[PDB]
Image (cartoon, rainbow, N blue to C red):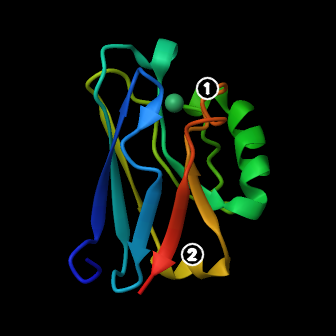
Amino acid sequence: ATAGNCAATVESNDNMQFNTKDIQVSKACKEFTITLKHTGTQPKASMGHNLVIAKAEDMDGVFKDGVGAADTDYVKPDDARVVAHTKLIGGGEESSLTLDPAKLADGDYKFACTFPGHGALMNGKVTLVD
Ligand SMILES: [Cu+]
């Protein structure tokens, strides 16, 4: 499936997991939407999740700058090394982002939760595909 997916939905729970560790972005899409749904009962301050997509080579700086942006859902208003980012969502809440697929051609991109203590496990691969 490539010509029938301009959006994706990721489910995160308070058991510390994503329902997918691989996201394939179609270059057939002008923009790609990713919707995150936190299917749990824990509030964002106790077990919050976000989905940040950035260049893997720069992913370290993304997490680092994310921790410094605690007031802004652990996402820093910048979007230079970061391609897209959701907000922190609690049990029942959802957040979404829109990214330019053609910007993922720079190399290997990853998606992860920039919540301190989560990124070590809550991360995967996001690849631009045809
Ligand atoms: Cu998280």
Q: Using a 10 Å C-alpha cutoff, classify the residue at mark 1 as few (fewer than 14 neighbours), some (14 to 19) or many (20 or more).
A: few
Q: Nearer the viewer, residue 71 or 83?
A: 83
In the image: residue 118, left or right of residue 49:
right
**Secondary structure at numbered mark 1:** helix
Looking at the rendered structure, the number of numbered marks drawn on it comes to 2
| Quadrant of the frame with the C terminus | bottom left
Q: Nearer the viewer, residue 110 or 75?
A: 110
Q: Amino acid at mark 2?
A: Leu
Above or below: residue 79 compared with residue 122: below
In the image: residue 93, left or right of residue 66:
left
**Quadrant of res 42:** top left
Q: Using a 10 Å C-alpha cutoff, classify the residue at mark 2 as few (fewer than 14 neighbours), some (14 to 19) or many (20 or more).
A: many
Dot placed on the residue nearer the N-terminal end, 2 or 1 = 1
In the rendered image, residue 1, in percent from the top left (x then y), is placed at 25, 77
Instruction: Give the residue pinned by disc 2.
Output: 104
**Secondary structure at numbered mark 2:** helix
In the rendered image, residue 108, in percent from the top left (x then y), is placed at 65, 70
Q: Amino acid at mark 1?
A: Asp
